[PDB]
Amino acid sequence: GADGVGSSSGNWHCDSTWLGDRVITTSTRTWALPTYNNHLYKQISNGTSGGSTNDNTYFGYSTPWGYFDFNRFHCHFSPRDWQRLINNNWGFRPKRLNFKLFNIQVKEVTQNEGTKTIANNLTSTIQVFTDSEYQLPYVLGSAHQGCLPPFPADVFMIPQYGYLTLNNGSQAVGRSSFYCLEYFPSQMLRTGNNFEFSYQFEDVPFHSSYAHSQSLDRLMNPLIDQYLYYLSRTQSTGGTQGTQQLLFSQAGPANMSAQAKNWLPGPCYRQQRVSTTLSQNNNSNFAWTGATKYHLNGRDSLVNPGVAMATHKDDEERFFPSSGVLMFGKQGAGRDNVDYSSVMLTSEEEIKTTNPVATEQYGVVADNLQQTNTGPIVGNVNSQGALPGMVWQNRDVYLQGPIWAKIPHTDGNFHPSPLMGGFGLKHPPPQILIKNTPVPADPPTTFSQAKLASFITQYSTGQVSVEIEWELQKENSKRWNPEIQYTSNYYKSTNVDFAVNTEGTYSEPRPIGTRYLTRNL
Amino acid sequence: PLMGGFGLKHPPPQILIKNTPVPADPPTTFSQAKLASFITQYSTGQVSVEIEWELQKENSKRWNPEIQYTSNYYKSTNVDFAVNTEGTYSEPRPIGTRYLTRNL
Image (tube, rainbow over all chains, first blue to last red; front, side, top):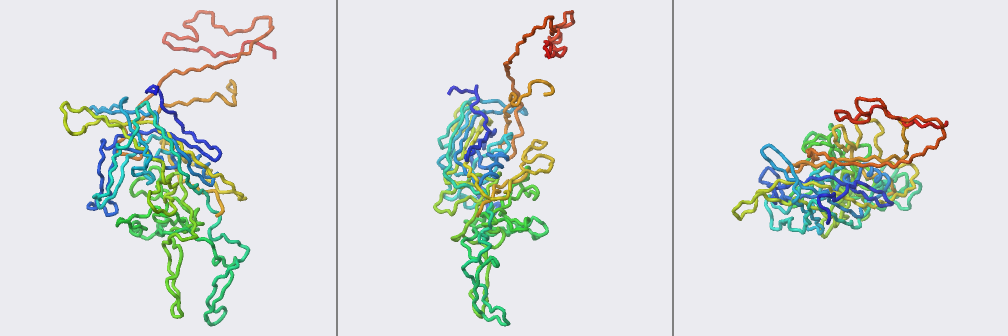
């Protein structure tokens, strides 16, 4: 080894490099791993016998271990480096990543009455194992808090680990699995050690970063008619009587709606439409009641976000689907009943081309069968499954949103793109679990059967580094006039955006979409 | 540069240094906010710098003596450019760089 506490195991690399198509972006932060659950696995459950309803019942365990979550973009891209990505490129996908712990140091805190003193414990060691066979519940991708902070000057606290399993009410059915974490081979790192591992993403499709320049129904040619015919009129034209006759015509630029087309909009699953204008919405609480839910195993679940769908039609920015759009918070936003002004509502408007309005009917079909005595009748289709000849475009990843998700290992899936966005992976980056090694206090002089319940209060810190080597899909486009670009406000402001304020508080003002450059549908 | 000294299009690169912040006890229950409690700390050490200079040697045929920078010959209460009774190093006067003479 020849290392010891005399040296620093690792150096600080926060550098990002743009090389040809590749772009290699690394980071580092400072983490403090608190002791969890006094080192006790615990069964946790929430029953429907309490005030909880049948939807909120869960069962599972909360482990002492804790896990690193880097899954979000803003970890790995500075708001400038995310500008060079969305402005200059069509698509990007990862290739490989690399991960390092270093400069690990441990501390143990004592209490004499009020006094509080904090010393180093050289002997104590921490346990790190990457779960590479996916043999645990993979809990990343559910958009939990605790990701590496955006702004490198922040020190973050590693979030606790724990999982859920099959429940029936509060109780547990027979198949409930219990995973004891200490049961996996886990390298132990002392202060002189570093930890490192490499991972190489599977081939995964380039995420689409462009807004189509042509709505799906305008793919026609404006000059020339079409050779096909449609049924224009069933009634006698230009007469005092409407006696029925079948008339046909050709579908030209005069009426473009009737022109035959080779494709269909993406699938549609309706959402209730809520207006930011307060006077327009109904006066009531319809939030949960009139929400769009799916019913599984007798447990209702609100559909958040829902499939990628255009947020609103043109000349209305105020309407948004109830649970449809991703919703972030502003810096320092309360957890409960936060006012509207403290949250940010992303907008899908770039997909209005190929995907339907979220809040409106997908289409209209005939309910009945006509007769001389009985006129035709047509109803709305709210939820339209996928049909052949349907093209849809995936939701764009945001700076704040997650990078990936694990496609569940099940027999059947249809175009497995995670709803929140980001690359679905059949073998995601393996999560990492880390814990202090519990160091017991004085055992008694006389042996006794029970396990030692008195532990030495302890927590450790260190520097963690991650690179993610990305592939950029370069952009070649002949469009004459200028594009749209993501640009900072030119007008004077009280404090700079995406940068600290007087208190030292880093505040990201607004979400940053990935779609700006344009392409032909 | 107006203050004098060599203007450089790529000067000596400045050096930035900071302690690595070491956080105090985080709470038992996880919480979103960054850790606001740090362990008061400061570091010390020895820094060394050399600067290798080139001197332009002086060749001059002037007959009579030059002017030279010389310390005061008369007795003084304490030595200039050196500590005083309190241990206080005091530079008494500024020292120009121009003494030797040359033909315009």
